[PDB]
Amino acid sequence: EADYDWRNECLRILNLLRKEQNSFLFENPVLESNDLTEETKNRYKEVIPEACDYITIEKRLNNKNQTIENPHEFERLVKLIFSNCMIFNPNSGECKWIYDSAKQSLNKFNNLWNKSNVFLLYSNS
Ligand SMILES: CCOC(=O)Nc1cc(-c2ccc(C)c(NS(C)(=O)=O)c2)nn2c(C)nnc12
């Protein structure tokens, strides 16, 4: 790595999830999106109590306005993005590609996270 900072190791992995298929879904807050209708955004607040997204996590890592205290909170927040998407959207029908996109980015995240030194950088800091 030759980095030493665990937060940059988190940002590196976040930037790699941005290159995944339909990554635009998880980039900005769904509740701020002008693309979705208010009807769907009002059901979202009822179904999802804690919304999250990549730009919100990225801004929380740069704090060093909340701040991510450790890799364990970063892991929670990234996985929260994919579980909210998989709770809100169906895994069957014509628009099942939204759920499937969350599922594949979660799978990509686990593979990057499991082979990362992010905890060894945090533990030795
Ligand atoms: C059939 C009804 O269901 C839905 O439309 N579902 C969801 C839709 C979108 C969504 C759409 C369009 C755009 C352009 C974006 N990108 S953004 C938020 O950065 O502006 C996201 N995100 N999403 C997330 C997460 N979780 N569920 C959904």
Image: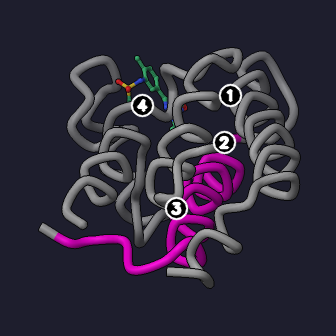
Q: Nearer the viewer, mark 2 or mark 4?
A: 4
Reading the chain from its start, which is encountered first: label 2 or label 4? Answer: 4
Q: Residues within 10 Å of mark 4 (few under 14, many from 20)?
A: some
> Residues at badges 2 and 4 in contact (C-beta under 8 Å)?
no
Reading the chain from its start, which is encountered first: label 1 or label 3? Answer: 3
**At label 1, which amino acid type do we have?**
Ile
Q: CA distance from mark 1 to mark 4?
A: 14 Å
Ligand 1 within 8 A of label 4's CB?
yes
> Residues at badges 3 and 4 in contact (C-beta under 8 Å)?
no
**At label 4, which amino acid type do we have?**
Glu
- In the drawing, what numbered circle is on residue 98? 1
Ligand 1 within 8 A of label 3's CB?
no
Q: Which residue is mark 2?
A: 89
Residue at disc 3, secondary structure: helix
Q: Residues within 10 Å of mark 3 (few under 14, many from 20)?
A: many
What residue is at 12 percent from the left and 67 percent from the top? 65
What residue is at 46 percent from the left and 48 percent from the top? 8
**At label 3, which amino acid type do we have?**
Trp
What residue is at 82 percent from the left and 34 percent from the top? 104
Residue at disc 1, secondary structure: helix
Q: Position of residue 118 (x, y in %)?
A: 65, 63
Reading the chain from its start, which is encountered first: label 3 or label 2? Answer: 3
- Residue in the foreground of this view, choosing between 111 and 2: 2
Q: Nearer the viewer, mark 3 or mark 2?
A: 3
Ligand 1 within 8 A of label 2's CB?
yes
The quarter of the picture where residue 75 lies is: bottom right
- In the drawing, what numbered circle is on residue 6? 3
- Highlighted magenta segment, given as a residue range: 66-89
> Residues at badges 1 and 2 in contact (C-beta under 8 Å)?
yes
Q: Nearer the viewer, mark 3 or mark 4?
A: 3
Q: Which residue is mark 4?
A: 27
Q: Position of residue 30 (x, y in %)?
A: 35, 39
